[PDB]
Each structure stands twice: as structure tokens, then as C-alpha cells.
Image (cartoon, rainbow over all chains, first blue to last red):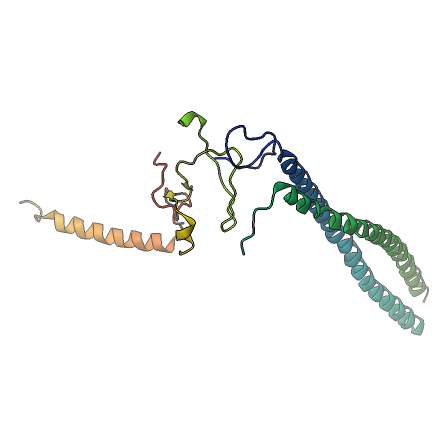
Length: 87
Length: 68
Length: 50
Length: 50
């Protein structure tokens, strides 16, 4: 029905496993550091997610298309000019 | 394998020792972002410019064709 | 020990280590949501044999 | 008897042919393995008979 995903708040005042007044700081600091690591991993997918998909795709895609365009244009121009002047 | 149950204060230090790798590698990430951004800007500019160039170029070419 | 303080909860096992929640006192039944199926409890000295 | 007697056999053979053709049609028609388990095929003895 539930998960144990929440954060460490209190100490066992009955129950001989887990938290005591002399260990709660450990739990809380562990939680903080884990969340900070996640912050990093997620922002990373992002930079990386972003970086990759985004710029890599706009760069390569249009450079290739535009250079094919270059070939085409140059060829056409040259051919036309030459043949017509010959006429 | 099966490890022992360290006292909490140690698991804390273990958790802490993850954040630093992340921090440093994020810096190189940012520097390189700036790079591919400058590159993309330059790219777009050059592309559009020389595209209009070839446009007016073939325009003058067809002009010369009609002249002939 | 009575119901009203009981709890439903899901677990994260990782082939073993599945850890005990702080709030724990004593365990009644434990099972899967899948198909309905009950575990039972034993000692190390037996599971190790298994 | 008036007409022929024992229309039972005729009607029964008719229904047999009908179920045969219906079976063929159903086999050739696309339909999933629909059931009340709702993806719980590996959850034998479902605890929710609701």
C-alpha cells in the first residue's frame, strides 16, 4: 500500500532498530547527500540531454543539408553559364 | 557478496563522497555547452548568408542566360 | 499489539538486504501483491543451507 | 405426424454447421486474450474477488 520514501524526521522512542538520538544526524545528512547527488544526475541528463539532442542535431543536420545545397548550386551555376555563353 | 552493517555516521560519509565527481564534470559540461553554442550561432549565420549569396548568384546567372 | 496501529507498506529488496524500517516493532503477515503469496520466516542456519 | 417428424436432428445439424462457421469466423478475426484477471496471469489466487 505504501513505500518508505519519506525523509527521516524522528527517532524511535520504542523499537530497537533504526534511529536513536545519537544517530539521527547520520540519517538526515545521508538523505541530504542523496538528494544532492540526484540533483546532479538529473541536471546532467538535462545538460547532456539538452547539449546532445539539441545543438548536435541543429549543427550536423543543417551543415550537411547546406553543403549538399552548395554542391547543387555551384554545379548548376557553372553548367548553365558555360552552355549559354557557348550559345 | 555480503557486507557488514557500518554505523550510520559512516554511511553518511559514503553518501557525501558522491557529489564532487558530479560538481567537477558539470564545469566541463558548461564550458563545452558554451562552445557548441558559439559553433551553432556561427553555423546558422554562415548558412543563411551564403544561401542568400547563391540565390542572387543564380539570379545573375539566369540574367546572363537571357542576355545570351 | 492490535490492528489500528498496523501498516501496509511496499518494500525494496535488492536480492536480500531489504532493510528494516525504523518504525518497526513486530511483523505479522508478509506477502506479494502478485497472485497472493505468503512468506514464512526461519533462521539463518537454514536459509544458508538453502 | 404431419410434416416429417423429428425436426430435432435437422435443427441440431443446422446449429452444428452454424457453430462451425462461427468458430472459423472468430478464429480469423482479431481478438485479444481478454479475461477478468487484468494482467494478473501470474498472481494465482487473487485476493480481490470483488
